[PDB]
Amino acid sequence: SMSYTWTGALITPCAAEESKLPINPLSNSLLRHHNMVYATTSRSASLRQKKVTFDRLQVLDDHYRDVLKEMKAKASTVKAKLLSIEEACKLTPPHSAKSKFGYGAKDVRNLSSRAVNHIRSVWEDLLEDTETPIDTTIMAKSEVFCVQPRKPARLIVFPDLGVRVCEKMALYDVVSTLPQAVMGSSYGFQYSPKQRVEFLVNTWKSKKCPMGFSYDTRCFDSTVTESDIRVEESIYQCCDLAPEARQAIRSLTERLYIGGPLTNSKGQNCGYRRCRASGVLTTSCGNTLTCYLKATAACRAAKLQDCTMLVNGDDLVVICESAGTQEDAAALRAFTEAMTRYSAPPGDPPQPEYDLELITSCSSNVSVAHDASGKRVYYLTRDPTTPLARAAWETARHTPINSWLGNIIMYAPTLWARMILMTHFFSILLAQEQLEKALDCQIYGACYSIEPLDLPQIIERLHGLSAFTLHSYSPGEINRVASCLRKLGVPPLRTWRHRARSVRAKLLSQGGRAATCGRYLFNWAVRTKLKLTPIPAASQLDLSGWFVAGYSGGDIYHS
Image (cartoon, rainbow, N blue to C red; front, side, top):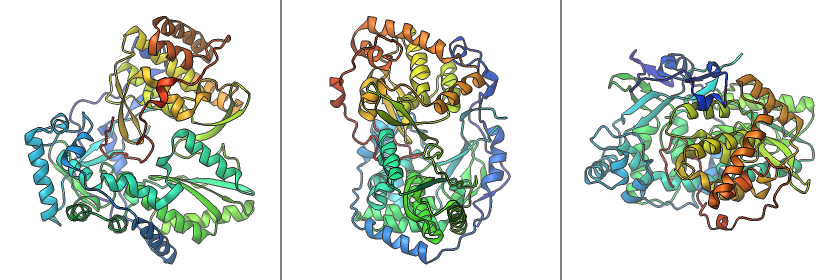
């Protein structure tokens, strides 16, 4: 059936939308070519609708049904708890969209009476109404990018805050624990950057002759079928669950997950959804499950030998035993025909890679460097264009999320993150004495509140001390970076070294947590380097739950 159906109404905005990068002295010292930095807006929604709207072809087979059974079997071992209103409430981001029922994120997190009552009723309705479609709002997402030699806005779809709290109560535990129990080590979200790189390298090294490939599904969310969603439910149904939870999962599937009406910000009726809603709690879990299912079965159909998979929602990367240049190519193609039939056509044509550094999964690739001792250290990196573009934007305008704080944390080892992202922001945070002001960044969909002063501890725990001494980066990685800088109009690395020297001096001058930031984050700025030793207060930090599960668009906030 058609992924979407439109009445004719338009996807509208609430407030005005800034699409151009301001001429700010602060952002300008970071990125000069401001005209190459844009933000998507509702004005392009139309194009995106034109791409995500199509008819889904899907033919199942024995391979598919066999992989399904296996997944169910593991599902059975899971026992999911029903969250309390209080618990689900504490999970709501402070700035989550308010309900159209006289209360907002702040009220929910505060267990206010009105909010709680409506939740109670929204919940009681999920237990009694097992059919009526549930209303969802559709909006144009606002994301920053760099022009190319422009992308249309992606469309977000979500139900009312009341429903979201109920989803958490009935499924937060399921989506936090089931992907793992089912996919085992193939479930990507359990790994921290360091751990993901560990898994990729060991896997590659364990193949007699490794062949790997990433697979890009053309608009995954619109490729997901009601059948996919119901199969996704049958898995959830294998868990031991409390009665009301079992009903909630059932009613949510029929009234929300499989599809439903779409309403713009003005209250008009835009159309109807019959595929994955990007903004629900089960979006990450379902996509990871669905994508894993289809890929596993496709892998068999294609006859790839000794496959090892890594799935992150819709992102997929496979590494296997190569047969031969030709065999591999013919097999990949067979794999794509499998996926196509399971309703997961390719966006970009899947190319078989024979060098781990060439494969790009989750927008990252492997690269090598050396620590103080010259020992080789594999780390995760990527083209820094978007990250830089967003730092600039986030510098000129106060945004809800700081993609830059997240990128530093996720790319603390990379060249650009240390030399630019760190230098630039600590520079500005000093000038505004906000080194202690907590900012909301985001990791795997989940929204975290973090104090810049903690970064050192965080980085040491998620990466290891080598993240402060990495050096001697590969030429390929250096060139991509320098190239990128010239393109955007960002000062050359030598300027950042100079700048980092200054910012460091100041940091140390302040003593305390800051003096540390300068010692560890910027030890690369000096030549008479300090011997960096484990940081005490780090291991005392609670980082449990940080790399356990993805929650893209899940409205999750545990900080």
